[PDB]
Image: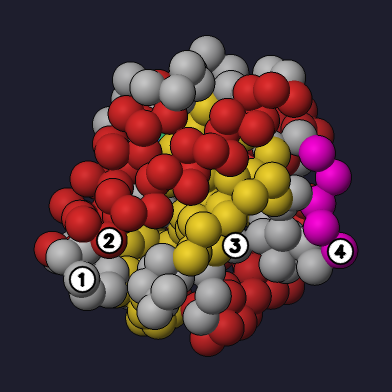
Amino acid sequence: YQPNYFLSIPITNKKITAGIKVLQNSILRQDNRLTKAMVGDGSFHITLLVMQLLNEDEVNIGTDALLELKPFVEEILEGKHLTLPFHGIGTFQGQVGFVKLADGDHVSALLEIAETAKRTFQEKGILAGESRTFKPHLTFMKLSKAPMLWKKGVRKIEPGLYEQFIDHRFGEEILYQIDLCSMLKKKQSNGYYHCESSIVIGEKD
Ligand SMILES: Nc1ncnc2c1ncn2[C@@H]1O[C@H](COP(=O)(O)O)[C@@H](O)[C@H]1O
């Protein structure tokens, strides 16, 4: 199905987003055609769950489901925090460029959160999740954003463009928030997606 909403973990570590800005700029100074493929300043996030919310009532149900999700996250994390190290560059078949999530224990925890989120939302009546295996990633560019590239002289991201960063430590993000975001509504003034609702993770209540 085609989703229109998603749960999003914003990247709150300014070092990570600043380092990705450098990476995007390094790429653009080599080929300015890639400008419209870059994700916008302020939009950096990890997608946790996609879904359809197709009317105002369903948007309100989604907000309720996210509120319900909060305690499950802290159960999964066992009263500690989830540290996400962002290191190196990966792609999905040269069409989407992302900063990779380093391997480690936090990957299984993040996967458990995604699966519990899917279950939580489905039990509230929301079509959510994907059949495809969840592959967490922090996108910096996607060719699909720039449909004239395909039609023109650029059909994949040349790996030479990001070679200097292929193995760069961007930084570590501690999970602090999950937002319910609209894919299609206008972005906030700070460049982030329209947010219906948000919960805090990892803080004293
Ligand atoms: N497991 C996957 N395999 C291939 N492409 C993916 C996968 N997960 C996400 N994508 C694509 O990566 C693009 C950017 O991801 P995102 O920044 O999370 O929206 C999305 O349009 C997804 O369709």
The mark closer to the camera, 2 or 3, is 2
Residue located 32% across and 54% down the image: 71
Q: Quadrant of the C terminus?
A: bottom left
Residue 162: image x %, image y %? 50, 67
Specify few, some or many for label 1: CA neighbours under 10 Å numbering under 14, 14-19, or 20 or more: few
Q: What element carries label 3?
A: loop
Asked whether the beta carbons under mark 2 and mark 4 sit within 8 Å of each other, the answer is no
Task: Return the residue at label 4.
Answer: 189
**Label 1 sits on residue:** 79
Disc number for residue 44? 3
Which residue appears at 27% of the width and 61% of the height? 74
Q: Earlier in the sequence, mark 2 or mark 3?
A: 3
State the separation of the CA atoms marked 3 and 1.
26 Å
User: From mark 1 to mark 4, how far is it between C-alphas?
Assistant: 34 Å
Q: Nearer the viewer, mark 2 or mark 4?
A: 2
What residue did someone put label 2 on? Answer: 74
